[PDB]
Amino acid sequence: ADISRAEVATLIQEAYSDTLLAAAKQGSTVLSAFQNVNMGTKTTHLPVLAT
Amino acid sequence: ADISRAEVATLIQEAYSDTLLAAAKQGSTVLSAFQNVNMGTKTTHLPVLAT
């Protein structure tokens, strides 16, 4: 005796949005606070003044 | 059945970097705080009022 929103089936379509999806990425702190030194092998030796 | 990094001994070289080596040097304080009198001899005499 009446048409409910179930009996209309897929003529009513659900909808989509990006609005909450995007999230900012945060880099390393130490890779921007300090000098990045290139390496070509596992170990690099650095001499320093000692006395 | 497997090669480990201990078994590749000295086919892997160790590198060097001077990026920590360069210490800066600090001058005398008294040579910048006060007048530098040029001398051509061991002794200079300066008279002053005394009474």
Image (cartoon, coloured by chain):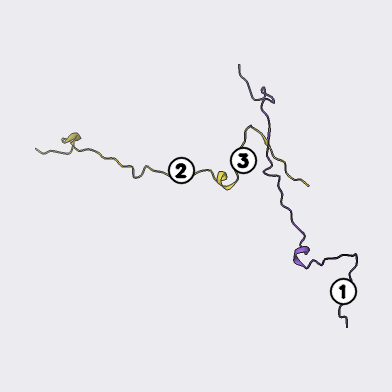
Chain colours: A yellow, B purple
Give the residue number, with chain letter if any, for mark 3. Answer: A37
Between B18 and B38, which is closer to the camera in this rendering? Answer: B38
Residue type beneath disc 1: Leu
The chain containing the residue under callout 3 comes to: A
Rounded to the nearest whole Å, what is the CA distance between mark 1 and mark 2? 72 Å
Residue type beneath disc 2: Lys
Rounded to the nearest whole Å, what is the CA distance between mark 3 and mark 1? 58 Å
Give the residue number, with chain letter if any, for mark 2. Answer: A25
Disc 2, SS: loop
- Are the residues under marks 2 and 3 on the same chain? yes
The chain containing the residue under callout 1 comes to: B
The chain containing the residue under callout 2 comes to: A
Badge 3 crowding class, 10 Å Cα cut-off, few under 14, some 14 to 19, many 20 or more, is: few
Disc 3, SS: loop
Judged left or right of residue A42, residue A27 is left
Residue B4 x/y as whole percent? 63, 23
Residue B10 x/y as whole percent? 69, 26
Residues at badges 3 and 1 in contact (C-beta under 8 Å)?
Answer: no
Badge 2 crowding class, 10 Å Cα cut-off, few under 14, some 14 to 19, many 20 or more, is: few
Residue B46 x/y as whole percent? 87, 74
Nearest to N terminus: mark 2 or mark 3: 2
Between B35 and B1, which is closer to the camera in this rendering? Answer: B35
Residue type beneath disc 3: Val
Q: Which residue lies furthest to the front in this view?
A: B40
Residues at badges 1 and 2 in contact (C-beta under 8 Å)?
Answer: no
Give the residue number, with chain letter if any, for mark 1. Answer: B46
Image height check: is B12 above or below B29?
A: above
Residues at badges 2 and 3 in contact (C-beta under 8 Å)?
Answer: no
Residue under the image location 12 percent in, 38 percent down: A3
**Image quadrant containing the N terminus of chain B:** top right
Q: Nearer the viewer, mark 2 or mark 3?
A: 3
Snapshot quadrant of residue A1: top left
